[PDB]
Image 1 (cartoon, one colour):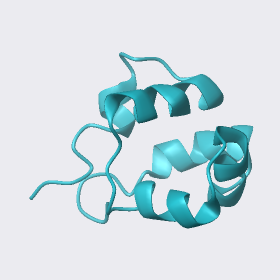
Image 2: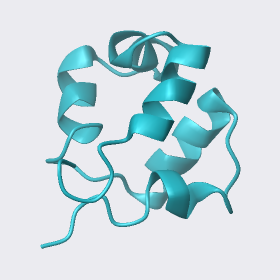
Image 3: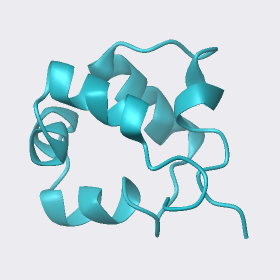
Length: 74
């Protein structure tokens, strides 16, 4: 979130693969409405949700703490 990862490194990959959060949604199979909740700060990803992003974005499960570790801390 604004505290603990503004997802800047992630967003780069998002742009690199999809373009934008909008397109992220599209590729992931989510709606922008939902993405902008989850990929923002309210609805922090579950492990399978992380995994699905990894599948789209082509990330690695070990490279995860760099993108999504806490990304929320309260």
